[PDB]
Image (spheres, coloured by chain):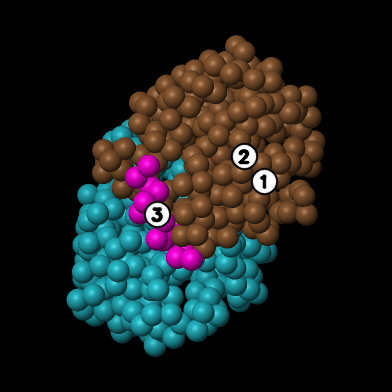
Chain colours: A brown, B cyan
């Protein structure tokens, strides 16, 4: 399944009661992942929602158009996807760059968003010292070279040692991400600072951060939550891909929040 | 992502290791209801010694699901057409379940295309009409969620499943999103393939890996397979049917030492 959205082709995947009547949840992935990263949440979510997952532009089985990409393109893909599938309004749960997209969507397109879960993210993620070298390395050396540095930021060393099959699966998706699509998203993320509009988010919002997350910090998640009136901040004992390392605690947090 | 139009279909494939290097090739072939992510625990170790080709079997993953039923000849020709497309002249081959079955066909009917074969959680005749006929009906008329609850417990021991809920969820996600017609047509292929008369004809070094808890393809069938094949060797792992996941480390080691001996 693929949807032509902005003259760009996105791979997507639906779970839950299709004939049924349940609210939608849209899930939005981290840089260097694909929609498989949400597999631990799919069962619980499916009990309450129709679930829409997709591969972000430049990722997974989606197209990689010419970059640099921008936050507005990443926001527009989600809206266009929902347009295509005739989803008038949905809950939204995004991780890292997925959370950043959630910020833009919630601030600017609340008529399309019911509730927002903003996970392992910040209103402004990283800095040019992170994103510029990362995009050069991606472009000039390929993704295999990048995995060694990036993957340790995603999971604690204990989790990786204990779970070499999960790590190998996640690493395989990262290392096979289109290097240009990857760099072009590095550019979108670096260019995006949504700090000015976080305070304009008026939908119910949950911010999840990982205690051990160095890519988007607990301080950043608290800053994001404090900007949003009524936002709830939850910290998990995890690093950056918290929905995997702490799947049960993540899933329970998000489901409880969304079914309020 | 990479696709090749081959044998009258389109297959999604993936290459690891230096693709223009000089290391021998290895082609991996997946189980029914999986996609090429199932071999992710082996990729790192095999990339050290080999150029690695993985692919989504027809009806699976991101490959096309053409009109079924499928046959063991379509499945074999798929591997061959992919190799041909990549200019791969010969390769080691490691297949799990229907992948191991494909590997028996390939090693028997295409010895010159094959270096060494690892035939994993498999048999020269897998299951029986009493399993495959209702399976195909169920997949086609009820969809894959229904099948997942019956099939998945046959792939891992209870304890692994309890200990490894993230691995299970990811494997289940691929299984439940398999095209149902694609899956049923492969059921038909496997049920029709009885490679037992052809196995004694295999001329290349073979390794047979079986899981002591595998009910879908048994140790006993693993031994018969190994005994049909001149010089084949048999190794049994403390696992059920998807042994390259449940006992990844031992599986990897076994396959690597055998293929590089
Ligand atoms: C791989 C599959 O879907 C069936 C295997 C079995 O007979 O249990």
Label 3 close to label 1 by CB (< 8 Å): no
Residue ID for mark 3? A147
Q: Tell me what residue is drawn at x 38 percent, y 77 percent.
A: B25
Considering the whole magenta stretch, tell me its main secondary structure.
helix
Horizontal side of B97 relative to B139 (left or right) equals left
Name the secondary structure under disc 2: loop
Instruction: Please say if B10 is above or below A11.
Output: below
Q: Identify the residue under disc 2.
A: A192
Query: Where does the image place residue B240, in percent across and percent down from the top left?
Result: 31, 48
Residue visible at 60% across and 54% down?
A: A184
Residue A4 in the image: above or below residue A108: below
Residue at 47% x, 54% y is A133
Q: Is residue A146 located in the magenta-colored stretch of the structure?
A: yes
Task: Residue at 28% x, 53% y: name it.
Answer: B248
The reply to the same-chain question for discs 1 and 2 is yes
Q: Is B4 or A198 nearer to us in this picture?
A: A198
Q: Is any atom of residue B172 visible in this view?
A: no
Q: Which residue is mark 1?
A: A70
Instruction: Identify the subunit bearing mark 1.
Output: A
**Where are the magenta residues, as a range?**
A140-153
């Amino acid at each position: 399944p693929y949807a032509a959205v902005n003259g760009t082709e996105l791979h997507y995947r639906i779970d839950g009661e299709r004939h049924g009547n349940a609210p939608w949840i849209v899930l939005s992935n981290s840089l260097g992942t694909d929609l498989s990263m949400w597999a631990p949440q799919v069962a619980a979510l499916s009990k309450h929602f129709r679930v829409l997952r997709y591969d972000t532009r430049g990722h997974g089985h989606s197209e990689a158009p010419k970059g640099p990409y921008t936050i507005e393109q990443l926001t527009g893909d989600v809206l266009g996807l929902m347009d295509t599938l005739k989803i008038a309004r949905a809950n939204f749960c995004g991780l890292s760059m997925g959370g950043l997209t959630g910020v833009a969507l919630a601030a600017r397109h609340a008529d399309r968003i019911e509730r927002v879960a903003l996970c392992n993210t910040a209103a402004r993620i990283g800095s040019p010292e992170v994103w510029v070298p990362r995009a050069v390395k991606a472009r000039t050396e390929g993704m295999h070279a990048l995995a060694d540095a990036v993957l340790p930021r995603w999971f604690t060393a204990d989790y990786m040692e204990r779970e070499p099959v999960v790590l190998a699966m996640i690493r395989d998706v990262f290392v096979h991400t289109d290097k240009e699509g990857y760099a072009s998203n590095c550019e979108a993320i670096d260019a995006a600072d949504l700090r000015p509009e976080a305070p304009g988010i008026k939908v119910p919002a949950l911010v999840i951060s990982g205690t051990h997350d160095l890519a988007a910090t607990p301080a950043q998640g608290r800053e994001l939550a404090q900007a949003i009136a009524g936002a709830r901040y939850v910290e998990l004992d995890a690093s950056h891909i918290s929905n995997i390392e702490r799947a049960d605690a993540f899933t329970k947090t998000v489901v409880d929040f969304l079914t309020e």
